[PDB]
Amino acid sequence: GVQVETISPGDGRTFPKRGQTCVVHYTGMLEDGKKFDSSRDRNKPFKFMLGKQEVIRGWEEGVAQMSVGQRAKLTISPDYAYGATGHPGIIPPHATLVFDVELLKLE
Ligand SMILES: CO[C@H]1C[C@@H]2CC[C@@H](C)[C@@](O)(O2)C(=O)C(=O)N2CCCC[C@H]2C(=O)O[C@H]([C@H](C)C[C@@H]2CC[C@@H](O)[C@H](OC)C2)CC(=O)[C@H](C)/C=C(\C)[C@@H](O)[C@@H](OC)C(=O)[C@H](C)C[C@H](C)/C=C/C=C/C=C/1C
Image 1 (cartoon, helix red, strand yellow):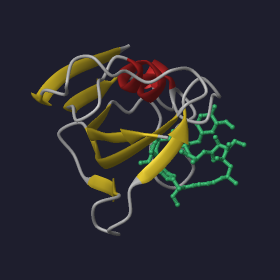
Image 2 (cartoon, protein in one colour):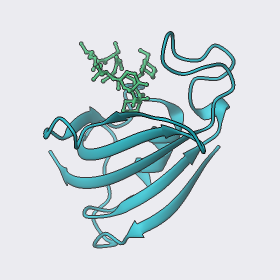
Image 3 (cartoon, protein in one colour):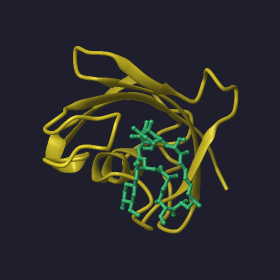
Image 4 (cartoon, protein in one colour):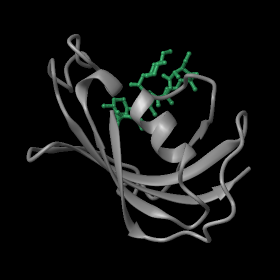
């Protein structure tokens, strides 16, 4: 599944609702491997709508349990990421992913 380890705590009260836009900064890497993506490097936060199957399961369930201002290490097993197929040209089959995700605001 997805393990969530807090890097910095949020307010512990303001959690995303289903259908709400989450505004996040993230860095993604293969577990004990190469960094493949970082929204911080392009200086523009990433946005997705929760409960719309817009992102991988590990992100859906991981961000759902985070409060505003929280920064966490998400360790996402293959079944909650890109599984046996992988993501063409970037993520190989059976890849465990590690994301550093900070929940900046809700809109
Ligand atoms: C250039 O950068 C890419 C993202 C890259 C792709 C490759 C991966 C390594 C990665 O580097 O991100 C990455 O770090 C990663 O794994 N991500 C992105 C950060 C959130 C978690 C994860 C993810 O789920 O990506 C996502 C993953 C790759 C595919 C989805 C996985 C869940 C599954 O249910 C979806 O089926 C549909 C497909 C990509 C996204 O986060 C984007 C935003 C969402 C989609 C494309 C779909 O949800 C789509 O559905 C029609 C939409 O509703 C969108 C909003 C419609 C508009 C027009 C499309 C915008 C496309 C944006 C693409 C962006 C910014």
